[PDB]
Image (tube, rainbow over all chains, first blue to last red):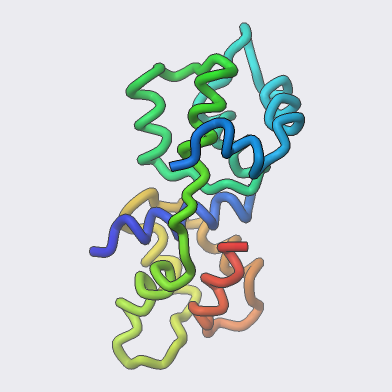
Length: 18
Length: 143
């Protein structure tokens, strides 16, 4: 559930850890 | 959604180009290295973005196709509320906290799943404590 917002969280985590 | 002109007011195209030169082979850049550059530029691509560009142009992007990809990565509609609501879904005691292990499950299960070690490292880098204030966490990753 709430998959699109999950994608954004994971996206920003990968951005942060780049 | 940002066009390339608007993208180039948001980020320095001098950086966009230098990062492309760093990763290009044969005048082209792979999606994965484009996503890497997007992140160095402060953008946050998901698999939706990657698959959209791949569907148009394949695995390797020309400079201009890379610019189009970056414009797709901008995500101006991103807000902290939607991130918080995603985590809050699992906070049924309404404590405001989830443990590192709970956070890990949430992040390594559905969607563009992090690896276990990726989730672990991001969580340990955020906090030395086991209870994660997920609102604080969301505010942190969005910056």
